[PDB]
Length: 135
Length: 135
Length: 4
Length: 4
Ligand SMILES: [Zn+2]
Ligand SMILES: [Zn+2]
Image (cartoon, rainbow over the protein chains, first blue to last red):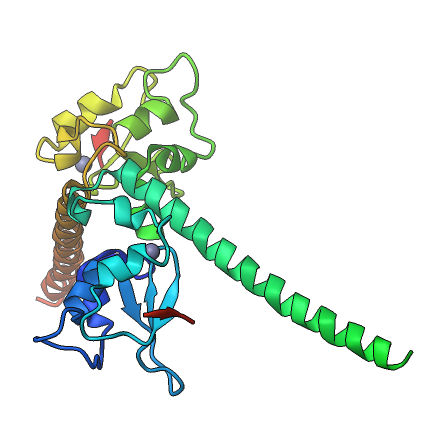
């Protein structure tokens, strides 16, 4: 079929990702409006409302039934390229699509780096405190 | 980077398939020229010069320096859709790309049916012969 | 909505 | 060239 590292790229997989979504017809953020905005449902015990853009990897929760996933998406990560893409996936050029997947993989990397950075900082401050206590 | 089943669509990959291809500069069928025509090297013992179309899976051997791999592809298998692809690759469309990959998977299936038929007929010839010597 |  |  279509390689399953690349599926986030098509709405159908994205909606499919919403196994249980609190919001539904009558509400502005349905799994369809969500996917259409590039969100994925990555639920957990502590937060099973958690959605994440498949492109820029921004995560967010505490959704409200009247939030519109698109403006909620511009007002949080404005630099998302996916937002700039106004054409259906199938009408994308292989070059365009490849450029896109590039930028994605990069954004993934930046996210993981930011993460490692914070983790390290925390550990840094722990160790420092300890050694200060010993003073 | 690209997903493995789909590499063959990429010229440089096809080219990279030619290892100890004897027809080198000066020749009409260079690995470059073969690739641009869709072939892949899949050499064996009896047939070290064996080449296969990736799209229609047609196979050809008995190569000679003057051979124009395009014109042999046209002559031997006229019906292959790859021959109709004028746009290189990355300027193609994802829609276009996946129609292509469908015909490819179809053609793949036609091929294994054909081989299955051939093994079948071989075995038949064997039992036939074997009944005759018993008659 | 709010950032994790 | 010829078919296999
Ligand atoms: Zn995004
Ligand atoms: Zn062909």
